[PDB]
Amino acid sequence: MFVTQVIFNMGERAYPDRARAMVAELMDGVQPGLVATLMNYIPGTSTSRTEFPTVQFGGASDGFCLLGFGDGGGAIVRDAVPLIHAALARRMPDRIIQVEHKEHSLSAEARPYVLSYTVPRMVVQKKQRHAERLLHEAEGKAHLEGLFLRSLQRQAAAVGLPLPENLEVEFKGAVGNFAAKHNPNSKVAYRGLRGAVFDVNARLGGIWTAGFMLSKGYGQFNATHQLSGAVNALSE
DNA sequence: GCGTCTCGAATCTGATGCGTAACTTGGATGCTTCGTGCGT
Image (tube, rainbow, N blue to C red; front, side, top):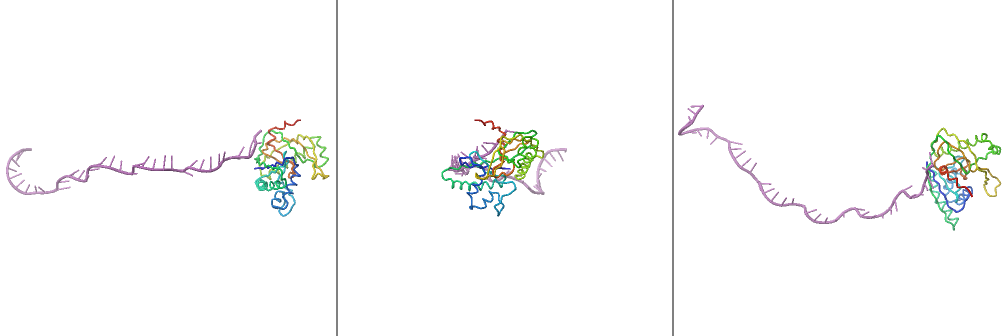
C-alpha cells in the first residue's frame, strides 16, 4: 500500500548498477543480516532471488535512490538508511550526503479510456530477431504487451494491491536505444528503450515498476508525476 | 487529473473572604346533682 523512496544526494548522477555494487561494498561484514536483507538473498546463502525484489534501486538525477515496497520494504529501508548513510559519510569525508525521504500511496483504479504512460528504462531485448520486429506494431505488440501485463500483475501480487480484471494495453513506441554493462571493462551489453509509451485504461498512483530485473535499476517510473505532463520542457 | 516533505511545541493546570441572624420555645375540654322555673 505504501512505497518509501529514499534519495542520497552525493552530487553526481551515478548509474544504478554501480550504486548497488558500491552500497554492497561499503557494508561488507558489518551487520550481515542487513546485507542479506538488502541484497535480496536467501537466508544462509549469498544468491539472489528470482522472485520479484522488494529492494529497489533507481538512478536519481543527483544520485541514487532506495525504494521499499510494502511494510517489509518500508521496514527494511527504515532500519537500513542510517547505516548506508554512515558508511557513505565514512567513505567520503569531504562531502555532505543528504537524504530525502518521501512516501507514495500505491493505487490502481480503472478508467474507461486510456492515458499516456511512458518509462525511461525498459528491458525489452530478448532476441535479436524481435529487435527488428518493432518496425511493424502487430508483430512486436504481443511480447511487449505480455511483458507489461505479467510485470504489472506480479508486482501487484507482491504488493497485494487489487487490480481490475479487464486491463488492455497497446504500445506506442520509444525514443531510442542505449547500451549498459556490468562493469566499464565488461564486453557484455544489453539494449533498452527510452520513452517507451504505452496506453492503459486505468490510473496508476505513486511510483510503479514494469518489466523484469528491476533491482539493478531498470523499469522504475513515476506514473503519477508523468500524468502532470511536465515532459514539455525538453529542448536546448 | 491526486505529489511528496512538514502533518508543532512549552507553560501555565487560582488566588481571598464569607463559611448567618431573630422569633416563635401551645392552648381548651372530657361532672353529675339540685333547685327553681319555664313551657311546650
